[PDB]
Length: 48
Length: 48
Image (cartoon, each protein chain N blue to C red):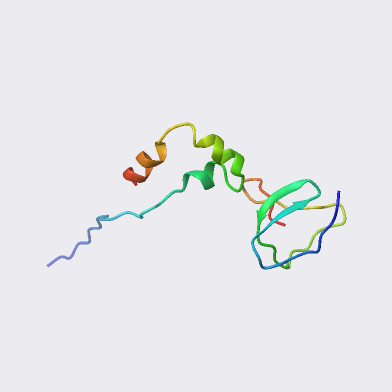
């Protein structure tokens, strides 16, 4: 694969480690743990 | 001389739904596949 700079606050396509999606990315105030990679909402769709 | 209270509902909240966002979401291939089923969306929209 290749790599590309990170853009924020614009609706874009993203491919994070095989996770494909379309949306806008924003800085987060959430706190994770060293054994976690991403979070989920009620409908088991990624949010962070 | 007595005063009594009665309560009666009148109205109800109004909702609207989107087909493609709920069923497919952010994937175009699902939309192109769903275009070949029917016109259930028209019925749902008319009822709502």
